[PDB]
Image (tube, rainbow over the protein chains, first blue to last red):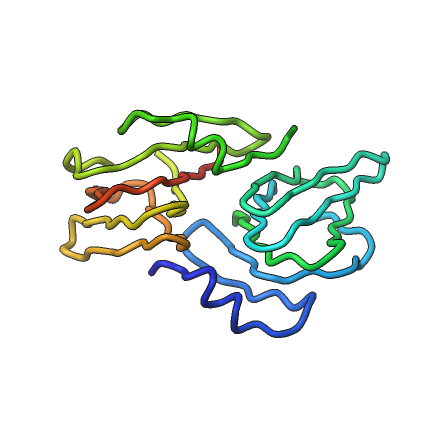
Length: 96
Length: 97
């Protein structure tokens, strides 16, 4: 059961509305971001910026840019703040 | 920095069943390019993402699975499978550590 990223992404039509998708050990989240929605926490996560750019602010002031075609990991337990200056389609890969 | 530009990492690898492997916290990334096949392989689960080009995966139970440019799928641990690519595929694998 392969997941067509462009497919599922084209369908979902609001920002901040994740489509969750399960596949064995892995949880996938597909969302689009614009703006920001403050701070979160949640094991490790893989964020893959399928379509625009995006950043994750950290509480201790650190900041991570995830430009298109880029992939990063947001460690477990660190309060953080995902945001997108101009809109980003994001796939997020999780465990349990 | 702590991010991975898929395209640029892949472009650096001009060999064929030669994974480059990157670590980032509790994740391991394999970047490898595929052409024809190398038979059956079987760990932990792996997510596969067909960064550029198409590929397929045969399984031991007879099923076979197309992963086209742009698509993800997962190969669970302890399932013998035969990864493979008709005209060549650049692919990211992902696992926990």
